[PDB]
Image (cartoon, coloured by chain):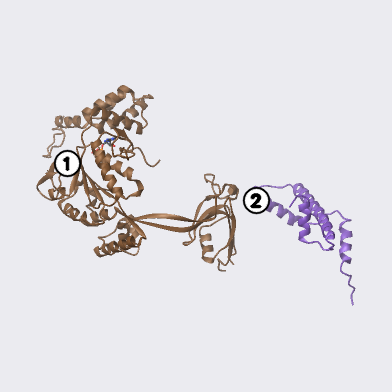
């Protein structure tokens, strides 16, 4: 389909026993990281429980230790029930809006308003449309519709006859009509009428007739974020800015009104509030102004849980000239609990490579998996994982059905790991342009 | 003052004319269009031989003439000189056809 194979495609969940929060040694595509997966499952529990507002969790650990994987596992194990916003900290440096406004919109995106509504929908195969069009139009007309179980005829009001002519509704068309709006969606063409569709090309699909009653109440559970309500109220087609962007800085008094109205809908029981998650990937790309805003945004009642990942050690905080752990100011780190991801053992690398060799269509011979595991220890999990794809392409060039050691060796030879790449750089320092701008082009 | 026959005189003259004759009583071109109109709903770009539609007039006129005879017996069984739609409906239903 349109989803290709990607680095996280094998993550199907968090891999944790829902009855106990005990992490299984591997399941759902996660291997090891058990203590970190247990902690993320405790966070996941209190996300679903909703009662706790504006807690922040940092996932801290060396690169490739599964920090994004655990974040993706939580997203896959929340699903559609809960809003889940992913933010790269690079994204808030907008030219359209100040970074605290961009960071406000991200918090607003992570609270859902859940609204349950009904409508009568009429659905069936058109047996006939008669419209007289009697000079003017839409004067009178009759609609006959059937399911497999019923047939009925309807006199149409003139603004429904406009809708029918607008949708060029024809005998044999399978339609749904939302009655209160009066919009007509043509779900398809009935197969029994196929010969009447003389203009439709042979690529055309056909359907069986709808089943049961022509009319029923269908109930829709909408979830709309606070950000969407904010943007809708900004201007006469405010929602249109939810797509193009081109929201300005939305005025604070609009948000304050909406917070009051959503509290009214909750107290009236018309709507429910569904707190989600905001995940801030590589949070150390934020600067000191951002962290000062976050500190108090977290104290709002309508704050999501915020989950964060950092590769950084004791490192320079952006927008200042001093250093702190994770690159995050201590006053912000006081508001945050930290989950640590550790490096992998060789057998866990073997399992992750095996999983990645299942997610791509690759057969690894047992010695090729052993060699990739050895390369994984020596050159890192990500590099060996990229040798899987490379080896399959080399094997296919030699038309082999399984990837052999010869293919992994060609991969290791053709594509350098980060350390050999650095060693190549440290040898070529006269040919590579230095930090001084100096370079020699002679042989 | 011009003559005028009694109600039922020319009906009998018409019966005695059409039971004596064999020529077809439905008009040709109006029946061709009915056949082609019906055929369109089964398959586009069909053709009919002239003999195929003329064979098909002869079949259906005989069906209608034969049905009217059965309905006329249903009328006179109701002691009516006048055939009515429920006579058609009775005749076909006895025939297993309605
Ligand atoms: N415990 C694990 N189980 C399964 N796959 C993992 C695990 N840890 C890392 N990976 C995979 O290895 C790759 C690198 O890990 P990643 O989560 O990107 O590390 P980080 O985000 O800390 O750099 C990703 O494709 C990820 O899916």
Quadrant of picture, ligand 1: top left
Dot 2: element:
helix
Q: Is residue A314 above or below residue A293?
A: above
A29 to the left or right of A126: left
Residue A96 location, quadrant: bottom left
Which residue reaches farthest bottom?
Answer: B1
Task: Determine crowd level at label 1: few under 14, some 14-19, many 20+ residues with C-alpha closer than 10 A.
Answer: some
Image hue for chain A: brown
Q: Chain of mark 2?
A: B
* Picture residue at 28% right of the left edge, 24% below the top: A370
Q: Is residue A55 above or below residue A415?
A: below
Task: Determine crowd level at label 2: few under 14, some 14-19, many 20+ residues with C-alpha closer than 10 A.
Answer: few
Rendering coords of residue A305 (x, y %):
25, 50
> In front here: A50 or A290?
A50
Rendering coords of residue A62 (x, y %):
19, 37
Give the total number of marks visible in the rendering.
2
In the rendered image, what is the letter of the chain coloured purple?
Answer: B
Q: Which residue is mark 1?
A: A312
């Amino acid at each position: 389909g349109l989803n290709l194979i990607a680095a996280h495609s094998h993550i199907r969940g968090l891999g944790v026993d829902a009855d106990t929060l005990e992490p299984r040694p591997s399941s759902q595509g996660l291997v090891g990281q058990e203590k970190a997966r247990k902690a993320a499952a405790v966070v996941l529990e209190m996300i679903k429980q909703g009662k706790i507002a504006g807690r922040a969790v940092l996932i801290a650990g060396p690169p490739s230790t599964g920090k994004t994987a655990i974040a993706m596992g939580m997203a896959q194990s929340l699903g559609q029930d809960v809003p889940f916003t992913t933010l790269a900290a690079s994204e808030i440096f907008s030219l359209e809006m100040s970074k605290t406004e961009a960071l406000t919109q991200a918090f607003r995106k992570s609270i859902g308003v859940r609204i349950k509504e009904e409508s009568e929908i009429m659905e069936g195969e058109v047996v006939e449309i008669q419209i007289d069009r009697s000079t003017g139009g839409a004067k009178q007309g009759k609609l006959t519709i059937k399911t497999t179980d019923m047939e009925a005829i309807y006199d149409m009001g003139s603004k429904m006859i406009d809708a029918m002519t607008k949708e060029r509704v024809m005998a044999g068309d399978i339609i749904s009509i939302d009655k209160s709006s009066g919009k007509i969606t043509k779900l398809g063409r009935s197969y029994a009428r196929s010969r009447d569709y003389d203009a439709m090309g042979v690529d055309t699909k056909f359907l069986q007739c709808p089943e049961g009653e022509l009319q029923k109440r269908k109930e829709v559970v909408h979830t709309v974020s606070l950000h969407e309500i904010d943007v809708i109220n900004s201007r006469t087609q405010g929602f249109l800015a939810l797509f193009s962007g081109d929201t300005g800085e939305i005025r604070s008094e609009i948000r304050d009104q909406i917070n009051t109205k959503v509290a009214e809908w909750k107290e009236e029981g018309k709507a429910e509030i569904v707190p989600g998650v905001l995940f801030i990937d590589e949070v150390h790309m934020l600067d000191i102004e951002c962290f000062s805003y976050i500190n108090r945004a977290l104290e709002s009642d309508l704050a999501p849980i915020v989950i964060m990942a950092s590769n950084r050690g004791v490192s320079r905080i952006r927008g200042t000239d001093y250093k702190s752990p994770h690159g995050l100011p201590l006053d912000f780190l006081d508001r945050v609990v930290i989950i640590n991801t550790h490096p992998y053992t060789p057998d866990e690398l073997r399992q992750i490579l095996s999983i990645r060799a299942q997610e791509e269509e690759v057969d690894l011979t047992p010695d090729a998996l052993a060699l990739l595991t050895k390369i994984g220890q020596e050159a890192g999990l990500r590099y060996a994982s990229n040798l899987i794809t490379t080896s399959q392409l080399i094997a296919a060039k030699r038309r082999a059905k399984q990837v052999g050691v010869e293919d992994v060796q060609r991969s290791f030879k053709l594509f350098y790991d980060p350390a050999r790449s650095v060693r190549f750089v440290q040898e070529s320092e006269k040919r590579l342009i230095g930090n001084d701008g100096v370079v020699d082009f002679s042989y | 003052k011009p003559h005028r026959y009694r109600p039922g005189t020319v009906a009998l003259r018409e019966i005695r004319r059409y039971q004596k004759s064999t020529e077809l009583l439905i008009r040709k071109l109006p029946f061709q269009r009915l056949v082609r109109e019906i055929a369109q709903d089964f398959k586009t770009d069909l053709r009919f031989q002239s003999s195929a539609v003329m064979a098909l007039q002869e079949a259906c006129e005989a069906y209608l003439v034969g049905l009217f005879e059965d309905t006329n017996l249903c009328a006179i069984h109701a002691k009516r000189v006048t055939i009515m739609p429920k006579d058609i409906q009775l005749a076909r239903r006895i025939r297993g056809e309605r």
